[PDB]
Length: 217
Length: 217
Ligand SMILES: Cc1cn([C@H]2C[C@H](O)[C@@H](COP(=O)(O)O)O2)c(=O)[nH]c1=O
Ligand SMILES: Cc1cn([C@H]2C[C@H](O)[C@@H](COP(=O)(O)O)O2)c(=O)[nH]c1=O
Ligand SMILES: [Mg+2]
Ligand SMILES: [Mg+2]
Ligand SMILES: [Mg+2]
Image (cartoon, rainbow over all chains, first blue to last red; front, side, top):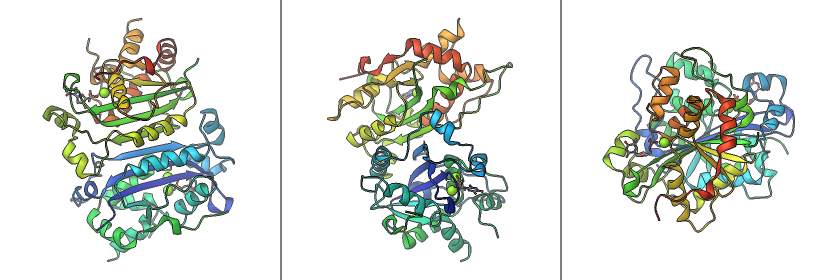
């Protein structure tokens, strides 16, 4: 193997891809290769939801968008533009790129971002947000993978919503759905089910983030 | 009403002050003053543990110390230098300072760090760790306050360990004791007990972090 760090990633946004959305919240949870492994393969029917590894770097940030959240977007995320602005949240800017860079630089390399439906939503959107900045992309040099593709490959070797996958493994609803941190913790739990097979698949399929096409722009 | 952000802060370290300890974990949770103000003032005996604000910025980092953790500190924190290093954790260095700076820069000013027993431990230690660096302190221009002093004012207006206060207030044991993030969450919950009274006290008693003397030279 060779990916040293998996960075679990989720985003909330102002709306669907067709509306040309902006990020309103993002979470990164960096776990070393070995901390993932040294969960068990979780035994029980159903198994208990595992505790995260002890050693973890986490970053969760709310981001003011330049356009308004759609009606449904505010209901499920519990974020709004007005509420983000009134609490002094800054836009997706150069300073956020430096924070992101400095955080990534603390992780052993190579690093692979891992996101649920990442190839269709999170990565394309993140690529668009960063392409607005004057600074070089902090995710240049990092890899990425979609956890849905991972889980279809591991499983097969009907709904694939994060919630549905989680409740099938654990027999409990996930908590804090559609919060970036909540959803990252939920995905981490799902990825602790067979972490050794996961890592093997990720080492096979990780692709440069630089080859992610932007959602729009 | 003049502190715009409270940043709840906890550190883990290699041991006690007489040993000349190094930071091995730090967590910062930034909450806009409006989010505290608009927490329900607690009612009941015991009141329910308060819900955290929706809009929060969080940073949690594990840090490789130069010297090993005392056996006692490893036992209570679940961290050791051995494990931090095998998981690729970096030292308390210039890049961590740039990261902290960028994080703080995203918060509306003035900012106030809030830490349980911060005056005798967290703040002097942090000041020592920042003094080793070539790059200027990112905490220059932030304020700070010890939440023990805050609660002593709000209470009287016997044990002041974090656990003792939490369970006196909420009749419940705290979770994830002696993890930086766990301890920050417990401190947030204690500070949401009388949030408006806490904010007024912080505003009156906050002091510049640059006046904090280092723990050791
Ligand atoms: C699932 C879903 C997502 N979205 C948008 C808003 C979310 O912040 C964003 C990211 O999806 P997520 O919350 O599943 O991670 O996509 C909707 O507007 N409506 C929906 O039903
Ligand atoms: C409470 C306690 C802390 N410590 C050290 C290890 C902790 O990481 C550090 C920070 O304290 P804390 O865990 O109370 O926040 O102090 C001891 O060595 N002995 C003790 O009894
Ligand atoms: Mg998502
Ligand atoms: Mg989400
Ligand atoms: Mg502490």
